[PDB]
Image: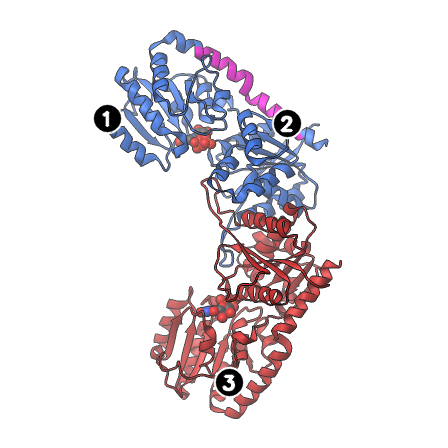
Chain colours: A blue, B red
Amino acid sequence: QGHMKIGITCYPSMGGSGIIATELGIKLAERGHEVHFITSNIPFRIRKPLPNMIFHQVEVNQYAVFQYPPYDITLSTKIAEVIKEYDLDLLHMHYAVPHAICGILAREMSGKDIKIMTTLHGTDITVLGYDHSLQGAIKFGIEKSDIVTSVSKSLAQETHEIIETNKEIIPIYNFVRENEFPTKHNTALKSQFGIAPDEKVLIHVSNFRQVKRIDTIIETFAKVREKIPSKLILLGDGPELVPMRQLTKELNVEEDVLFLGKQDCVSEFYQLSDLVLLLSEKESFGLTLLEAMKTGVVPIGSNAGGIKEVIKHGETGFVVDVGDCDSASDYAIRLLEDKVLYNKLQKNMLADIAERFGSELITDQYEYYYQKMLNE
Amino acid sequence: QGHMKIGITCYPSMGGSGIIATELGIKLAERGHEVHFITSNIPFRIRKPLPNMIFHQVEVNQYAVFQYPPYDITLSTKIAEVIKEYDLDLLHMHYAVPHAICGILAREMSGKDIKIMTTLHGTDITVLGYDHSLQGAIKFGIEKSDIVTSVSKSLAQETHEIIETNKEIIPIYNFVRENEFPTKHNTALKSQFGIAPDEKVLIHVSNFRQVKRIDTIIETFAKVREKIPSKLILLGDGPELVPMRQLTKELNVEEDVLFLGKQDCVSEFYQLSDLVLLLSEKESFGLTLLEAMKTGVVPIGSNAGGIKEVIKHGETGFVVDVGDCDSASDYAIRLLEDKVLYNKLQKNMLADIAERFGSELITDQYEYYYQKMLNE
Ligand SMILES: O=c1ccn([C@@H]2O[C@H](COP(=O)(O)OP(=O)(O)O)[C@@H](O)[C@H]2O)c(=O)[nH]1
Ligand SMILES: O=c1ccn([C@@H]2O[C@H](COP(=O)(O)OP(=O)(O)O)[C@@H](O)[C@H]2O)c(=O)[nH]1
């Protein structure tokens, strides 16, 4: 037990997973562990440099000989070079593919029997939904990792179902860094963005993929809007943006839906919101829910995946069946009309997420299993 | 000794290397070995199906989760699946990167201690000329292979110099399949392509990269052309095509240089040629020289790399310093004016390449080292 030398690999900019992996490394470095990120040359935005937190980055070039940019090999070579230069104790890889495989290859290249934790975020299920070429790679990356974790219990279950492995998968929930998301409401920025100070605000934040079911979110909002003057803020960009814009026209809510594009400072938008919606068809955890909940925003989610673990239906928010804009709008109208209900769920919610998703508690759990695999 | 179950991975369409790897597999399958190609979905053009020669191919898709198409992992997974399904004895990987690494990863994924031969074609030197990110991967792929071969002695020497490894590298020359390149001259197609039946023809065949020094070839031809009515045929396409077209204008040989594009049936063009030129700055072997020489075409090459092993200066052709269009044109004019010299070099050449580069002899050498590593 004690100080560890840790190599972390993730996609630092790809959604929730990259945020989680980065914030976890920062928490570990603030405790005094020696933390090495090894990623491709993708930006990070670290605010305070630490001498014990080093970001190693690799360029993936094509050369005229490779048919494809050799990400897996270039990354594995860089991980192995950090293992040798800094005598790393363990690797923490995010995603079975490509990153568990990269860590396994880097272990071979380094000649050191380093321990490997792999954390599953749900992308390995997504890949297999498109085609089964990688079925054997995902099974191998899971089974040759020393410890495997998943960001929800639902994801651990789904993994066993789809991958067909006896490998133990440890559910360890996601978290937000509490000082990045102060619990507070602020109406100062509302006018800037064309929202009247009193107006109710519903927010959704995502990559605008079809799996997010923004169609259900806009349909929900249209039903809300005819009872309650309100705005729907949609943060992000992606494949469904134009079809969703068109949907707001067909439902006659175009002037009330704000497509604000990608935003780095999401905290300030949660601070002006009244409800957060994540009605996804598939979702291992749902980090935007937790970011909003920590801010104090009461959530409505679907019952897909881990969302029903994040939200306690009827206690800290509401959960609806996938695609049920009737029930979602019913709950939203009640929450926007009923301050007693809103205050009660919000109070329950703030206590619950402190209890189950606090950054200190989750970091302790990862740290515990780092040490467990180092002692096996 | 005897029958082997062999997995071969190469880029089937990338230059000489892909031709060599494919033709070697065909030779092995014709002997009765069980030959499995495992490549990405890149065409092959096999003329006769054999029950003991199977082409496995893998799609490399992006999925929205991978930042780069995961070639290395998808290929390694497919190799491992063939190892398990067909109980392969050994892998023959072409290129230290990516393919030696893929074979090494596939060995881990398969759970079988399969033997791995890696053949170096020179691309690993080229990659490192552009940047040194992959230095450690190339060393690892070489050192963790059971046997490493190189297509020339020059390349083995260069590898030791640049990679800094004590690993034994076995020079095994390239070959052409003799019935694909009958020794014969044919003027029937000359008129079709705007060449008078008697006109002397110089040919060059390449990927039109700067390393091929087609500028030296066109400068050589311009000096030839003012003494001898003649045509320069340039087969292929690539980055230097437009600058080379412009060069033929500046030298006033535009009407005498035929840019014929990429050609699959190169044999028919060698059959109408009088000289072949390969004046490359870097070149591990120079397969187009051997294809032309087997056809009966006398070569002029540079002294780079393995070209001076393929050509015996003054005996089976001529070798010049890189960029020396003065000497190259001097030799070319002599060969095109002097049938005694031409016939003598051509006779020496046809005997020499039968002795050192015959397909049966080279296949025997690969087969010998397959068996050697299976017995170690
Ligand atoms: O404009 C945006 C959109 C998303 N996110 C962040 O992206 C994460 C998860 O979003 P996403 O839909 O991209 O992927 P998934 O949640 O499915 O991982 C959350 O931390 C968001 O705060 C952000 O910062 N700005
Ligand atoms: O139009 C062409 C150009 C090249 N090649 C073949 O490509 C190989 C080697 O060519 P390249 O310059 O592409 O690569 P390198 O020789 O450097 O490997 C030889 O077998 C050629 O016959 C071909 O078949 N048709």
Residue type at numbered disc 1:
Asn
Does the residue tagged 1 have its C-beta within 8 Å of any atom of ligand 1? no
Whether residue B81 sits left or right of residue A237 in the image: it is right
* Residue of label 2: A367
Labels 3 and 2 within one chain = no
Does the residue tagged 2 have its C-beta within 8 Å of any atom of ligand 1? no
Q: Where residue A373 sits in the image (x, y, percent)? A: 68, 32
Pair 2/1: label in front: 1
Q: Disc 2 versus disc 1: distance between alpha carbons?
A: 51 Å
Q: Disc 3 versus disc 2: distance between alpha carbons?
A: 73 Å
- The answer to which image quadrant residue B177 occupies is bottom right
Residues marked 3 and 1 touching at CB (< 8 Å)? no
Image quadrant in which the N terminus of chain A is located: top right
Residues marked 2 and 1 touching at CB (< 8 Å)? no
Pair 3/1: label in front: 1
* Chain bearing mark 3: B
State the residue lying farthest toward the right.
Answer: B376
* Residue of label 1: A252
* Residue of label 3: B331
Badge 3 marks a residue whose secondary structure is helix
Image: magenta residue range: A345-370
Image quadrant in which the C terminus of chain A is located: top right
Q: Is residue A282 above or below residue B16?
A: above
Is residue A39 one of those drawn in magenta?
Answer: no
Q: Nearer the viewer, residue B350 or A258?
A: B350
Q: Where residue A226 sits in the image (x, y, percent)? A: 26, 18
Please give the name of the residue rendered at 67% of the width and 59% of the height, measured from the top-left corner. Answer: B164
